[PDB]
Amino acid sequence: ARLSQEIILNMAEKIIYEKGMEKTTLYDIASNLNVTHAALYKHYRNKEDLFQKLALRWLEETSREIFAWTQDAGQTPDDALHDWLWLLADTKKKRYKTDRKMFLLYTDYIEQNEELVKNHVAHLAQKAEEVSGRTNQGNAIITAFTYFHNPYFASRWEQAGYVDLFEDVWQIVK
Amino acid sequence: RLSQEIILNMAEKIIYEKGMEKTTLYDIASNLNVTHAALYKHYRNKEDLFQKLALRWLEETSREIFAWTQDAGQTPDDALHDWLWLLADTKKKRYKTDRKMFLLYTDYIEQNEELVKNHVAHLAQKAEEVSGRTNQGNAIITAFTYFHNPYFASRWEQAGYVDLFEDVWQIVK
């Protein structure tokens, strides 16, 4: 009779949501799972590895639609590029609104991690090229829209002019 | 006896070492050894004083950015390119030249809506004045956000900085 990786992950997430990462230890997670401390270690060496897997999981799940996105038949690559960028923007904004607490926590955590951040942006750049058909411009395009998807600016996405600014930026890159 | 300049200089000396949160006016008056309410003539509040110090620091940082102008014969596109590079290089070198100050004033300005709004609005004007792309200023600054927003400072030394800047320029020009 043994723990599952997901019951550990899940319990960790519950505790983090209650009191934040900084105050959450493997000992807290074991205790709440009614299991001896040492049993956690075969899954996670330390809370940092466990925290990294949580953040990545959240990032993976909240982004599935951005990466799975298809255009409607009859869209030009440009119109598709536009609609996809809007969806990316819309998706980060929506999440900030409905999952605010964890958005802040995970998004903070991911940004402080160079390898994770680069990986994510690499994926965004690839998708961008797949949809637009603009070879090797994917980075340039993602970066040009930094304001609209980087979480630092999330608290500014409900201000007057957001849409027009998005459209205005799009006019330059189109 | 007392001058705005010596008040500011002492205030900036103090928050440099303990930061705005902790620093009080009491701390400043006592540090100037000047009487108390003698300070209220100049600043009835500490947030007033910090904004002044912030503004003053932004002016000096960006002076060269607002002073720049093109050479005869340059196309507006090229001049926009060069100005955008100067804008980025300036933020980058300020971060290297004094991090502590860059952190403390940047931290404060970003959280002050009107202060940032004004500054990006100024940059937007400049971008139009240089480029001639009327009404597109705000969009052009917004497009280059990665290169001048201080949140990104600690990245500007990573590999591919120059190249990414060029690639962004290629799609906006």
Image: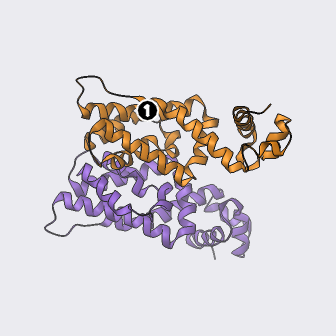
Chain colours: A purple, B orange
User: In what quadrant of the picture does the C terminus of chain B appear?
Assistant: top left
Q: Decide: few, some or many residues near mark 1? Use Cα within 10 Å; few <14, some 14-19, many ≥20.
A: many
Asked if residue A29 lies left or right of residue A165, the reply is right
A158 over B9 or under it: above or below: below
Looking at the picture, tell me which residue is in the foreground, B94 or A4: B94
Looking at the picture, tell me which residue is in the foreground, A129 or A115: A129
- Residue B76: % across, % down: 25, 33
Residue at left 72%, top 48%?
B46
Residue at left 68%, top 68%?
A19
Asked if residue A112 lies left or right of residue B36, the reply is left
Looking at the picture, tell me which residue is in the foreground, A147 or A43: A147
Looking at the picture, tell me which residue is in the foreground, A24 or B81: B81
| Residue identifier under label 1 | B65
> Which element type, helix, strand or loop, lies under badge 1?
helix
B123 over B44 or under it: above or below: above
B83 over A172 or under it: above or below: above
Asked if residue A4 lies left or right of residue A89, the reply is right
Residue B147 visible: yes
Q: Amino acid at mark 1?
A: Ile
User: In what quadrant of the picture does the N terminus of chain B appear?
Assistant: top right
